[PDB]
Amino acid sequence: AVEPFPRRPITRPHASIEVDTSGIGGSAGSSEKVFCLIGQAEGGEPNTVYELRNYSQAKRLFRSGELLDAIELAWGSNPNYTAGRILAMRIEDAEPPATWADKLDKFAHEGGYYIVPLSSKQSVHAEVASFVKERSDAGEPMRAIVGGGFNESKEQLFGRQASLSNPRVSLVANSGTFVMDDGRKNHVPAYMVAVALGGLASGLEIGESITFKPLRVSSLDQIYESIDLDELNENGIISIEFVRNRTNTFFRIVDDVTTFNDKSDPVKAEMAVGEANDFLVSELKVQLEDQFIGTRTINTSASIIKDFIQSYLGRKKRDNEIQDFPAEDVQVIVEGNEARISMTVYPIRSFKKISVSLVYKQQTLQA
Amino acid sequence: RKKRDNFPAEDVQVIVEGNEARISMTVYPIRSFKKISVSLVYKQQTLQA
Amino acid sequence: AVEPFPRRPITRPHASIEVDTSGIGGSAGSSEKVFCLIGQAEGGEPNTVYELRNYSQAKRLFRSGELLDAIELAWGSNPNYTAGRILAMRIEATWADKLDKFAHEGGYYIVPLSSKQSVHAEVASFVKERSDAGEPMRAIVGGGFNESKEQLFGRQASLSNPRVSLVANSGTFVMDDGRKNHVPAYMVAVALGGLASGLEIGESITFKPLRVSSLDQIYESIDLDELNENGIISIEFVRNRTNTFFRIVDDVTTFNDKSDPVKAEMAVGEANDFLVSEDQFIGTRTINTSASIIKDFIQSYLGRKKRDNFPAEDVQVIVEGNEARISMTVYPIRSFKKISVSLVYKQQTLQA
Amino acid sequence: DKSDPVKAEMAVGEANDFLVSELKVQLEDQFIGTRTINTSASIIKDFIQSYLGRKKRDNEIQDFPAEDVQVIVEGNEARISMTVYPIRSFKKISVSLVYKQQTLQA
């Protein structure tokens, strides 16, 4: 803005100052991913959302229940990365709830992106799928991560992936044994592994894949063979590989394939680039809206909007949230009611194939 | 000549009537944006080293 | 399609983003040439098509039978090539009702593990019924343990079809258990089908080696020519070297015709089954036209394009009923069957 | 078949096997799942040249022409090309020995 000093005008001879702050006013940084959990628990009032920052704070707001273990796994499984905020909600009817759709809505305008329901029921999975679709269509992009029960055959997994083929749901096959800060080792259903994967994905930078990131678990109940893992990967089911040929044995997340059945478009198939797309569109929308709508269509606006877009995309390039962009494709056309804007973006892709061609050749040494 | 020192032929209208000629220019006032339309195209690029 | 963001339309003042994803879509490439087998086994659930990915899985599902020996040969003839997927089905008589099950399993070569000519005719009929549909297929078949040339000719004539090949020879394969397994010629056909599945799209099995220990019959050059000209595949014992080996003479087909490569030679038929095929200005821009000026215009256009990036003798134009069809010739990649060397002895004056 | 040394000779097949195995395992753990940053092709080229430098140091290859190391990154994948001169044991020596006269004067 620009402001007069004094604010009240003066008629008689005087000096007055007009001051412009746009050059020092800040700007919104890169948005933050926040992780959402819905859980059976003991503790605080049900059906309200708590922002949580510390395990101690969580262990005061909640006690002795699977939600608190889920929060523990969510922070503990990503040691290398900054521990983000978590949004958590106990659920009980004011007895077991018949439906969660009535409660999921209380997340709707929270600043939250990844959802995990702490239950195995396919109906709950469908409910959260519908909710994530709803909010995305409303313009609040979200994703869900989903998992089975304690132990499931490939047949059951394929059945579930049939029941939910969706670009905003991911299914986690493996269930395993974790080790807890309480000095406890517990067998858990696969959705707790999905909690771990959501913690890692929400910790990672925007547009960074969970594929081939390590996972920390005491054991897995199902150790899938190479053909088994290829089968599940073809079906768009996330699987955990036990690395055995290395001297050190550890568990990899094999891939970040969504449950969606068509692999031809990566923006729908792969979580990372879909997330990058979601954040890029959301930030473009909200920033252009608050920047320009209602402003006067002064003759130079065709410059100013191009300069704004080029600045924004330069900032996106700086953070490695896009690969590159052509500056000259940023083009603006102004008509009396409307700004029409064109841009090209090169998005950032994770490496998923490396092909080495090795040519043996002779050289004649002589002396 | 004036705009060289300092208008589109498509934007001036002339009517002559009764020894009088009315010359009417179009002019463009300043409005305010109500709509912004962004077309976002994802290309891809070969890097090489 | 172009995606609107938000998905919901809005009329109050707002921004909306339209996303063109179409510049990134992929996976548009071909299928691999999955291989198909039908025959006897123990253990497997009959008339169920199983995908198989390694021999251990095969021995886990199928056991103790000729289908597993076939799967062994199918990956043993081509050790220096990719060991791709195989589709296999235990069959516990009509075979069409079983062959129907392969109809929507995406595999290109099939071999029945039987020498019975009724079976071969059924398989040829199935290959026809599939390939005249949107999903091309081929089959390979063989005789028994020893059949005469006149029997092989009679069989080929009865089974004369542009998508079936007959292999004449039979022999012995060393199995990975060390067994000297004597096998009928249709297992040699399995071995050739495995090789052909392993080779690239429009590579050819002619002059590829066969890793076989011995052959029941060794054909001299005149007999190899006789079988080749009749469209029967035969295996040569290469004797001209201390490093003797067995060589697939040719990829001929039981339909033999000099006038069309695509039906005579299996590899070019496969290329045609897998090849891929690849601007308008409208007469209102001109008062009248003819095929002559259409040809000269399109020649000037493609001359400009090929300068930036076609022979006038190689474009045909027909105009009919307000429509002009412009037909280019194009040249596909074949494979050499003949090399002709003219060697001229000159002599030279040296001087010093 | 003596024609191919990678088949005929144990030492060459061994060197090949360890070369391709350590390439696969290290490119896997170094780069798979990493973002295609605009510099990624240069980083991979440096990594490959480092690896081959080590293999040369240890006398596990004869040499590599470092200019032939080429990397192309295109969307979801990298294609890498390299030339390697393999290490080989001597298995023949031929000496051609020519007698010549010399005139001595004093």
Image (spheres, coloured by chain):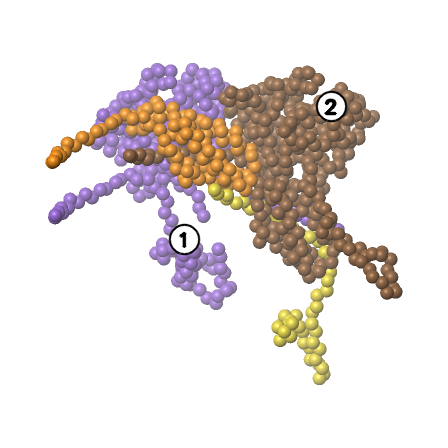
Chain colours: A brown, B yellow, C purple, D orange
Q: Which residue is mark 2?
A: A68
Mark 1: amino acid: Ser
Q: Position of residue C131 (x, y in %)?
A: 43, 37
Q: Which residue is mark 1?
A: C327
**Which chain does the residue under circle 2 lie in?**
A
Mark 2: amino acid: Leu
Quadrant placement of the C terminus of chain A: top left
Image position of B11 (left or right of A212): right
**Which chain does the residue under circle 1 lie in?**
C
Residue at 57% across, 31% down = A211
Comparing A248 with B25, the one in front is A248
Residue at 67% across, 60% down = A300
Q: Is residue C11 visible?
A: no
Callout in the foreground (1, 2) = 2
Q: Is residue A313 visible?
A: yes
Image position of C150 (left or right of D84): left
